[PDB]
Amino acid sequence: PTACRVCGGGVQEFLDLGRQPLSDRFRKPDELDDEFTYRLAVGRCDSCEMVQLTEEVPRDLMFHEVYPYHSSGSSVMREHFAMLARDFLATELTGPDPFIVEIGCNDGIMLRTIQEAGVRHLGFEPSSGVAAKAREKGIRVRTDFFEKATADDVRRTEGPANVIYAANTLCHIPYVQSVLEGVDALLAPDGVFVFEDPYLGDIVAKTSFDQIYDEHFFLFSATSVQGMAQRCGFELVDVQRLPVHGGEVRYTLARQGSRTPSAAVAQLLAAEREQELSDMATLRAFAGNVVKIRDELTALLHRLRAEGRSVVGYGATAKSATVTNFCGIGPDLVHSVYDTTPDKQNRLTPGAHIPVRPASAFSDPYPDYALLFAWNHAEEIMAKEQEFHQAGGRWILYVPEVHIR
Ligand SMILES: Cc1cn([C@H]2C[C@H](O)[C@@H](COP(=O)(O)OP(=O)(O)O[C@@H]3C[C@](C)(N)C(=O)[C@@H](C)O3)O2)c(=O)[nH]c1=O
Ligand SMILES: Nc1ncnc2c1ncn2[C@@H]1O[C@H](CSCC[C@H](N)C(=O)O)[C@@H](O)[C@H]1O
Ligand SMILES: [Zn+2]
């Protein structure tokens, strides 16, 4: 009976994905087979309806000097964030001396556009290796976690921020109340705090359980986000659904009563209520479909082997740690995983220990099948791998169901 991180209410578990490793730790082949593990389980608060994990992994075990995810490895996402930056430049950052703070800037994928507009800005990036990649682009970055105190410090030296933005970061931070206190300290009275994160609605519709892993503490909805803002003096004033990362919502929070919520907020709220998205029964039905997908995927993977078909994976996603460890999938079933990230190549996946090789190594002679872990990048990947499919190689997907095509 863990206490909700937003409100302190009681959290009821609906899904247990068992013992899991750190999702973003990629070991050299000769490293000790010891890994940090934790119990990955998800529940819903009874008071505010926030869906959240039941065990926190300490921040510093996940985010540090060698954290390996590089945002700019995706062309879709480079475009996606450059367009978002231009939109803030045309709307919220038209003053004499605007200021935008990004929480979790990573390699600078969004802030580069703000820096090239000459606008004052600051990225928080506690993972110093990717922080340095953003600094190389001329971005101003602080290697610190955003929380109340570091926000107070930026308020004291730099003044208020017109925009605070976080993408695929806010749902990573169990200490969201501290973040929100920092937002309260730092945001201009007429500013916005905008964040976008994997949306509970899409996870349930797609049964995309690999969206649940150490770094995703919260599975936000419009319902839980509205409650969360309210309990903090903010108000959810816009929502926009996004296709990226398997389905997200971008939430816009403002000081309460400062702006009138768009019709979009009330409409999404009513669709979630109508679909009973956060009801414990809907969430338990999702958990039972997760089990059906495990059972189908392992049966397929085993049949492929019995039929002497070769199988690899494509994309060394954090998400895949859930898949391989919950389903029991290792190198006997999926021999290698191909990935464009240097820091992940010539390493082994967490827990399951499948070797990671450069994507340039996925080439003729192709394997018979590629299990598509980077399924949120399907179009971008398939576009670069038409020869594989032309050769008769096929993709195994497990979202929204197990199928080959
Ligand atoms: C586009 C492309 C990617 N790839 C490779 C690169 C990446 O390792 C991985 C994709 O990881 P991708 O789905 O983006 O994020 P991941 O689940 O890891 O999750 C990471 C961690 C984090 C912050 N917790 C999160 O939520 C998201 C935003 O990022 O796949 C190719 O090989 N070829 C390609 O053409
Ligand atoms: N409290 C916090 N403040 C700011 N960044 C944080 C943080 N906790 C984690 N992070 C950073 O959040 C980043 C998530 S990776 C995704 C970053 C990028 N916005 C994108 O959408 O692709 C990591 O680089 C991690 O170091
Ligand atoms: Zn709660």
Image (cartoon, helix red, strand yellow):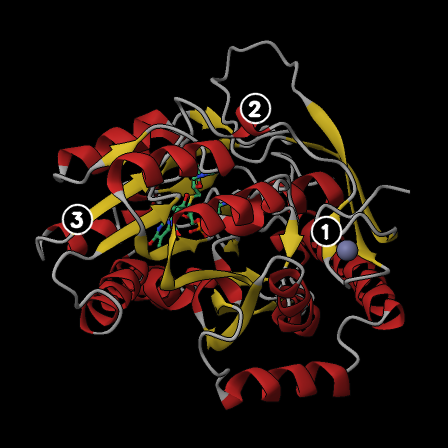
| Residue shown at 34% from the left, 41% from the top | 155
Callout in the foreground (3, 2): 3
**Whole-percent x and y of residue 353?**
59, 28
Q: Which mark is residue 52?
A: 1
| Horizontal relation, residue 261 to residue 321: left or right | left
Crowding near pointer 2: few (<14 within 10 Å), some, many (20+)? Answer: few
* First along the sequence among labels 1 and 3: 1
Looking at the rendered structure, the secondary structure element under dot 2 is helix
Quadrant where the image shows the N terminus:
top right
Q: Which mark is residue 120?
A: 3
Circles 2 and 1: CB distance less than 8 Å? no
* First along the sequence among labels 3 and 2: 2
Looking at the rendered structure, the secondary structure element under dot 1 is strand
Report the residue marked by disc 2.
Answer: 61
The disc labelled 2 sits on which kind of residue? Leu
**Whole-percent x and y of residue 5?**
72, 45
